Amino acid sequence: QRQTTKSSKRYRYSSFKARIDDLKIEPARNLEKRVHDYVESSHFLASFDQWKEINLSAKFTEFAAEIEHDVQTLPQILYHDKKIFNSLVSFINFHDEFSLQPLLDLLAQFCHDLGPDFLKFYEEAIKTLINLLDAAIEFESSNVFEWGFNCLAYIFKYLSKFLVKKLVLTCDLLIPLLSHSKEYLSRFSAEALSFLVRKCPVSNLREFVRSVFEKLEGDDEQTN
Amino acid sequence: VFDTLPNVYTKDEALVWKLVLSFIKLPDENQNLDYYQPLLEDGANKVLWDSSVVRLRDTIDTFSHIWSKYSTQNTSIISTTIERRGNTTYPILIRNQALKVMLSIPQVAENHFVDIAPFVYNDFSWTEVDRNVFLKTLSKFKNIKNVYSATELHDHLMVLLGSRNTDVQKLALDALLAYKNPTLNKYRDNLKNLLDDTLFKDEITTFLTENGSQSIKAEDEKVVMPYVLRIFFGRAQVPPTSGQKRSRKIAVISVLPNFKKPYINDFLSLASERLDYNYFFGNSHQINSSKATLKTIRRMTGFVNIVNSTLSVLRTNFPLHTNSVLQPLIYSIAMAYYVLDTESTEEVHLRKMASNLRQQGLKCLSSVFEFVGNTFDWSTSMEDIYAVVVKPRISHFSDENLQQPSSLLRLFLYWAHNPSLYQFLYYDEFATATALM
Amino acid sequence: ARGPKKHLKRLAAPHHWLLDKLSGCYAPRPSAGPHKLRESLPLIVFLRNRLKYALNGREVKAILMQRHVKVDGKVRTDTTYPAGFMDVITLDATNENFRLVYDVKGRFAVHRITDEEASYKLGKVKKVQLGKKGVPYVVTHDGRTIRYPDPNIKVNDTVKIDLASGKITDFIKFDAGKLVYVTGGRNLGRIGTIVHKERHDGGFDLVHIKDSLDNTFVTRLNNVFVIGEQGKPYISLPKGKGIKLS
Amino acid sequence: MKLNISYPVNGSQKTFEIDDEHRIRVFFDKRIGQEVDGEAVGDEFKGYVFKISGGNDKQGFPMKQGVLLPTRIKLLLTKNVSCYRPRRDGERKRKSVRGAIVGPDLAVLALVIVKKGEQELEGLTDTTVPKRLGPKRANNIRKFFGLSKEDDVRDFVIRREVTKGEKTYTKAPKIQRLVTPQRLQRKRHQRALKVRNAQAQREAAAEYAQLLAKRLSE
Amino acid sequence: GISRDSRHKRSATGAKRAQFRKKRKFELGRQPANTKIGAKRIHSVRTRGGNKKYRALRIETGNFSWASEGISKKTRIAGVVYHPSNNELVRTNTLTKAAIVQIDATPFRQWFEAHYGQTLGKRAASAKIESSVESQFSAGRLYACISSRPGQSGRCDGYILEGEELAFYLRRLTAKK
RNA sequence: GAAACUGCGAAUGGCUCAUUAAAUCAGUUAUCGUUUAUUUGAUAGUUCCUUACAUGGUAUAACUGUGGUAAUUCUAGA
RNA sequence: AUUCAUAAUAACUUUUCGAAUCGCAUGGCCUUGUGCUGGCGAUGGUUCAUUCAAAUUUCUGCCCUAUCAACUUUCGAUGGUA
């Protein structure tokens, strides 16, 4: 019996598990005036300025110092990609709740700008994401989960074609999240991979389904 | 049915009694449904697949269950046969049902009682509420002096008065006062008020202290002290957790020193009789059964604690008796040695309570020597008390006892300072003297 | 009046809150707590009137109930909590710590504070006694009871207190030549060194103090508060450093 | 007057108008809580036994047990009493209330049936009204159903079938004082927290005595 | 009806003050509880704060201490003997503080016999006690001063009158007889 | 989530200036002479001590139902 | 400045207190028992400290009246003791 006749009041309680069970993933199902989609001098820089004005936290302030010194223009991004990426990953691994919304948001936008060159960071980008998600389990924060899985969904959305072409490796990368022993990890990670698979065309889909069924025989004992 | 039956037992007051007794005996009585069990058949398999969606799981389960039953048809024939056969177990409360009926119609029990006294003299096992309702019946009896076994009932009834639950004590006084005699008629209210918790201490100092108004008289005291003694025994068994209850126990012991010598000795006899020592003293020093239970150990512990307080309150005037105080104390300390030697160190709780028992008993012996000492003989028991001194102690007395004056060492020193008691030093090859050396 | 009062007029407020005389008829009466009525700053007067992070009482209550404000490490949801002197109020979503300390003009000055300095708090040892079961305790100037103190901590001292554990990291004795902050009367906000302690038995001990420009004033022991040794304060002093000028 | 009679065992009740001063005189000068005879009252009540349980006089002032005056009095009524319900904490109103001894001036006399006679009263003894609510504590369910301590309650709760429109529906009360894994967890936690408290205190006290001894040995 | 303000009094100069304000509950009084000897009965008055206060209306027994060797025993109170405020209280057998009552001896003498190996009347250096106390024991009743406030704590506690105490009170009793 | 029980508030606020001439009040002290809801900080293993703690007991409200009176924020019996 | 804080002894008490309460969670362990452990916080509870208060109180200070010069003390006015 989930809350179905709303109380007249305005501030309810909504424990953690309630929030997560109410949580879903799709942003295109979602919609709003996205800043990066709005202004176009560069997507990363757009989000970067909005967040510098909005977020006042130690980690993001440090990160903003370093990078605002570096990036101001798309050629500068393209030239200094590695330094920016290492900085983002350094802070994400710092795992600070107050700074993660801007850091993950900037990561998604960083891929959006850098698309077909982002693949050389792709693998350990994903490693860092999954580490963050397990640590988030430790320090429960439904907001953290919302941000992290939306970063994954956005990365898939921006790198649709290449990931689709090399689909099965993505499934191998996500299988820790996919078979993870937590209902909502299974639920969300599968929703992201769901977007990607629905995008995929027929032939790679056949290869994918074969590979995943043989993985199922691999984890025959596992049910998750 | 409870509102009907008390009008028709009159029409039949024999079959109703038979049914009542049948139920009383009934739950303790064994019930068996050892039905016919055929040979087992291992016919079973994963007939269908296993899915996650719940209602599919459910229907698959129903089908698999039916399939399993049919594959193992034979035993399942038996099982379905049983379930349609139905039960024959009387619910366990049926004894309380019958007892409540018995309460409803007391005079029938007062009539027969022949099949009831076996329960009392077996001391029931039964549940506390059932015991209580049965004692309520016994209070409801009218001609109680003329029951089947009046005096054996009376003894068990005194024991129930000696019990510790104050409600059980109230019921036992109700029965013992259903027994009619003018002295207890005179002291009815006094005893009932003594049981009542609030008026307890005021009552003690009211009519128990000697040479006062409303004091008990001589013939009266002879006939009533056993009741008073059992009541005080329960009051003492109150365990001392709070300041108020500590004061309660202390008040009981501190009114003790005014009764009389035989009465005090009899009170201590109560303590020992709840305890036991004819094991050794029908043997010599050898335990018949390895009854090393916490049960008997805490029994001994309560006995020695009651004795320690008794000494501390009567420390020169109290009587000593070999068959009521001296011997059971010795049994206690001997048992402590025995258990401590016999069982390993895995039994922490037993071991700790045994050590505490040994401490308390030795302190008690030291005390009693200090406190009566020369005032009566020991020759009858010198050998035995020396024995229980010296089995474990003289071996390592010097090694163990050197930091503070121990109770045992104080015992030895009293022996030495008193001349007529040189007999222990004498009694061994001066093992005690050499230990001191 | 037949019981405690629950209201505070606006003219009757403590003056150092700088409350305008027309915006309303009532002022936030500070709830009972660590600091006395008249020398405390409630969280609404701090979050709305000083920080300007709010515009209403209902905005201030929204902030508190959303659980942002911690007064000495613990989360406070009472909107008239009497935050007092030498207090540490942290707003994490803004990444700020505030030591509440007096400005030269008398008023509470916001003092922005870093994390390693927000980690602790000074307290004026004010009553040393022997508690039940024989454990001795100190009572500081904001209610705090601290057991098992150093035996050499005497009344009128300072103890630097680790907030994360409610414990005493160390202390400072009330001797001549220490640095002194002043918290009452005409000179409050004035930091100087303690020259003399003229002590009267049965009356009020006065203290003679000398600020860095060698200007001397006389206050009461009730109003002296020892901060640190000469030239090194244990806390970070607000600007101007308690020098009254022309 | 009017006789408001009730059979508690069926819990039924009716009112009968009464006119004959003969049986009214049967009633006079008896008090609330005495006993009467249905024979002496009338023929239909043959063999019945009533106890005088209450009533109100012609102006509505009810009978109060305790006041032994067959008239009306002014009583300073206190918190936990009958014929008055306090409106406020610690409030005592002085109310007018009618005495206990029965007289003529009583308008409604209220009786309960103690011993059923030999004849059938129409609405009282024929019919009966079932209980509104069944047990709610664990042990009260157990007592109502005579259950053995082994058996669990949540299979024996009393549900109620209500219906709205076409959808039927069932209700069951929450069994207050049921023994639950949550309660076991809470008890376990209380014990652990006491242990932890005492250990912390002993550690601090040993540390302080350490500091003090070091000082005295300096 | 019992109130204890100082504004209904004449001033120090002997002036008379006109009433200043209605009487107040934070200066009330209450009816004295004349404690008498008999079966125990103790009302409990509720006092400012939530506190309690056990008025003793009748009290029989008591807790009395022998100071000289330092023990305490619960005894019975026989009757009031002397009272330094009202011989009327003595007449009416009213227990209050500072009263002199005759108490039962038996618990004390039993402790004495059992602790000092010697009877009373008819380590001996320690066993030696005062002549007057010995005489009272021979009689069976002791003189003891009630030293608590039965209207404030519902108790009669007391001490047994030793040397100078007892001398003074025996003179007072004998002179007043 | 109505009703009702339980907890809390209702002792504040607002209004008037009748009384009151060392009274009030003002500044200044004392409580080593006392109560204090609340807030805030600390703070309560007692292992044992002779014959359910997987958690005792009975009531009562609202409610169902029978009624009274010219009438009230009246209320009786079950 | 204390018969202070605090500690100790012996008793006493119609005698208190020493958690039978509630929310969200579902982790750790294994002798696989529906066993053993455990997280965040609501409420309450004794004794001190604090805070919001309160009650009493020290010193000094009031307008017109001497054609009001004696006042207060049974009926408390001043002091002592209980």
Image (spheres, coloured by chain):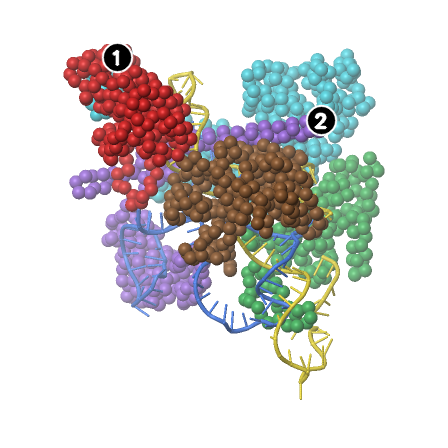
Chain colours: A red, B cyan, C brown, D purple, E green, F blue, G yellow
Residue in the foreground of this view, choosing between B211 and D46: B211
Mark 1: few/some/many CA within 10 Å (<14, 14-19, 20+): few
Chain name for mark 1: A
Image quadrant where residue B412 sits:
top right
Chain name for mark 2: D
Residue D109 on image: x %, y %? 33, 61
| Amino acid at circle 1 | Lys
Residue E82 on image: x %, y %? 74, 57
Q: How far apart are marks 1 and 2 (CA)?
A: 72 Å
Tell me which residue sits at (68%, 68%) in the image: E12
Q: How many numbered marks appear? A: 2
Residue E83 on image: x %, y %? 72, 58
The residue at the far left in this view is A202
Q: Describe the element under mark 1 as helix, strand or loop.
A: helix
Tell me which residue sits at (56%, 41%) in the image: C241
Q: On the picture, is B420 further left or further right than E9? A: right
Q: On the picture, is A41 further left or further right than D28? A: left
Q: Are marks 1 and 2 on the same chain?
A: no
Residue in the foreground of this view, choosing between E137 and A135: A135
User: Which residue bears the numbered disc 1?
Assistant: A215
Tell me which residue sits at (62%, 53%) in the image: E152
| Amino acid at circle 2 | Ser
Q: Residue D217 carries which label?
A: 2
- Relative vertical location of residue B292 with respect to residue E4 in this rendering, above or below: above
Q: On the picture, is D126 further left or further right than B410? A: left
Residue in the foreground of this view, choosing between F63 and C238: C238
Q: Describe the element under mark 2 as helix, strand or loop.
A: helix
